Amino acid sequence: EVFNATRFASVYAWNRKRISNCVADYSVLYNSASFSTFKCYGVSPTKL
Amino acid sequence: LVKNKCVNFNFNGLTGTGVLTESNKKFLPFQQFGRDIADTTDAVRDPQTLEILDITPCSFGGVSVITPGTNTSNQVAVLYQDVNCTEVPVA
Amino acid sequence: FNKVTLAQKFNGLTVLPPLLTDEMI
Amino acid sequence: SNFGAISSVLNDILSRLDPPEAEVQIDRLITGRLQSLQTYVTQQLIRA
Ligand SMILES: *[C@@H]1O[C@H](CO)[C@@H](O)[C@H](O)[C@H]1NC(C)=O
Ligand SMILES: *[C@@H]1O[C@H](CO)[C@@H](O)[C@H](O)[C@H]1NC(C)=O
Image (cartoon, rainbow over all chains, first blue to last red; front, top):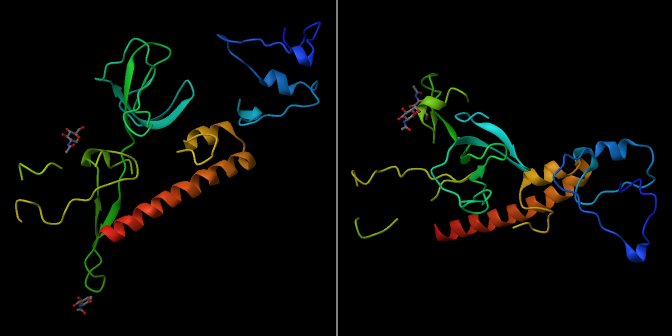
């Protein structure tokens, strides 16, 4: 519901969604060949 | 969970190696983990159940070799500097 | 001895014992 | 003391980062810790 939202907010009115109390499998994100940019800072995607 | 052997542990992103034992120290209702001195995680409460764990660092020390002159004899004895004798056989 | 008051357990750090114990000094 | 690293424990850095990215932070920690140990040993030599 965050990545596949039908409408996106303008960058000057950026939204914010809090995620908690769940198991996160981020491998689903960067394994998908659908993102032109996937850059991390202070953490590594392979070990997330 | 195992207790009386040195083990690798990862508690909710807290990684370390040591021996885990039932803690005499008593936590306040929802303190998470103690650090007795110098930000060493000396204890942690389990996330799955709610027991309190006391952590003692992995037993370690210096090994030294006692020897008479190799001129005179070849027999040699070895001394482990800081360990109880019952737990040396591992290393 | 009873007047003078006198390293905590930690990683890396270690304290050797003195060669002559107090009982023999 | 973090010495300007991401965190103050080797385990956090080596669990958060990949080898080219982790190496610089580990070096940042190593240089500071080595300097502190050198100062301590020089002080001990003078006091001895
Ligand atoms: C062997 O060498 C040691 C080392 O200096 C010396 O103390 C000892 O007297 C020597 N013994 C013989 C038989 O050469
Ligand atoms: C060494 O360990 C054994 C078993 O854990 C124990 O019975 C003994 O009292 C210990 N001795 C010392 C000096 O720690």
